[PDB]
Image (tube, rainbow over all chains, first blue to last red; front, side):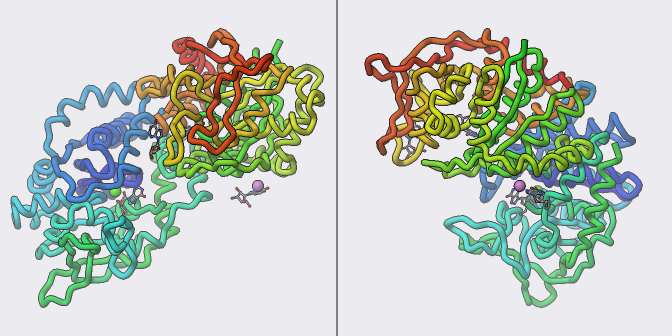
Length: 314
Length: 317
Ligand SMILES: O=c1[nH]cnc2c1ncn2[C@@H]1O[C@H](CO)[C@@H](O)[C@H]1O
Ligand SMILES: O=c1[nH]cnc2c1ncn2[C@@H]1O[C@H](CO)[C@@H](O)[C@H]1O
Ligand SMILES: O=c1[nH]cnc2c1ncn2[C@@H]1O[C@H](CO)[C@@H](O)[C@H]1O
Ligand SMILES: O=c1[nH]cnc2c1ncn2[C@@H]1O[C@H](CO)[C@@H](O)[C@H]1O
Ligand SMILES: [Ca+2]
Ligand SMILES: [Ca+2]
Ligand code: NI
């Protein structure tokens, strides 16, 4: 298996992505996770990450791993409308079985002392083999590592698989001050995203809205987790999807198996100016600008089957 | 021993916790029917979630099946709502989509699709051998329709109506640019129907207004205790519903009273409803009209008793 670190923002799909990575131990060795106070209040996101990890560790062969809270702060905050979703998951019955919460209470102190950004840097730089970073939240943490360590960090990254942006499709950030061209993860911290997408020597796979828009969350599919209620992960995943696109989950599925999508190189820049299109990921013709491999035409059925099967790991 | 009960609800998360409380306490309650109104949910979703809960309960605790109808009631004041979706999410929850339960619901869904909720309530009440208790957790439109159509022929068959709604000596929860914050949502949705119900003589009414429901909030550590009971389908269900709206136990408290009146003492108050288009439209006010019908308003509910009742009830299966 290959080493993977999950850098997420604590929304429901970030957690479905976590389940996908953690459950596929033959292909992925999940060596760490960091949570950013973005799509969630870092507090609850950290706790849900820990509760899911402990539920899996006590039920399948998933080694414990470090979990760190990132110190990253937003340039433009997510809608408070969907930030406290990690708070709700923190209270779900399936994540509060006493034997699992007891394990989390026993290992929480070791994890509370990590600073997420430094943890991402250390896990990547100190690994024997290269590490794949699955980024389902903003790019603030990867940018921080690039700024502090440069090539000492990027040379140890196998690839960075990123959920974010919108290249040849409309974005999803519709506010009185914006024009709808930007996507939320990039809009949260444009400058950090600029740093990541313009870094030479860093291989980037980009799951922008171009690909995620083609694999929507539909009721008949979500109801199939009801056929697997003897599996804790199916009660977990079905409950989170029961609450609009499998953005982060698609991104993580690619990490598990690249047959999820073909990718095409595009030089991607980011608008960091305080304008209506702030956060937009745009094609640039600047000479020698670094290429990003944008996912295209994802294999929907393959992904949907992968998630249902993965949710039977325990 | 058990008494006949009909649940008249609006499909939000607490309407469903109320349903589980009534249905799980078979020593005390015989649930003979339910109707769903297109108020705090899109009614088709509320209809399906009611059916799916009933079928899970029939297959796991022998709950007898009963008719479920969608009401044709339309709002006087619709919510400018972004929360009428907590029935849709629910319809897709894994614990309500177990094959053996979905198969049974699919088998009986067409028969229930044919009912019209308002007429169904009237028929359930009027054709019953023993009197019927109506637990109303959504707006009062359906009870009002029955009173308007059948009058005493309907009310004489009602044991009592236990209603969640209103605010008597505390502020309300309807905060809009044109309101003064003294009205509560179930009444504000259809004030005229509420006025009809509260002013009907010869109808016994118990009222769980914000005065009592404000005293029992949904708190995270208590909700997390349902995780100690995941071997019970109803604990995964109730816990999941209270988890996503950690909010008060408005409807659940109302249903708990139907199960055991020790949940709260009640005090008689003559209640009128503001129907004119004023800032306090929908408010429940104490009227001084001579000989006006009394409503028994719940006071100082037994919170610990209620919280224990719900955790216990959720171990029924
Ligand atoms: O409406 C929403 N609800 C929950 N999460 C959302 C929503 N919109 C965006 N994201 C979050 O931002 C990225 C996609 O733009 C994904 O990483 C997702 O977690
Ligand atoms: O009466 C009905 N019978 C069968 N399905 C129905 C009915 N009403 C709504 N649906 C809905 O249409 C799809 C199934 O054809 C499902 O989405 C179901 O929720
Ligand atoms: O008690 C109250 N609390 C909060 N807002 C209120 C209350 N009463 C009336 N409004 C009104 O509803 C809008 C905010 O939702 C404001 O326009 C305010 O005038
Ligand atoms: O903020 C809210 N979210 C969801 N349901 C609500 C909210 N406020 C009120 N109710 C609904 O209206 C009655 C209490 O006024 C209860 O019947 C409850 O189901
Ligand atoms: Ca995310
Ligand atoms: Ca209600
Ligand atoms: Ni239908």
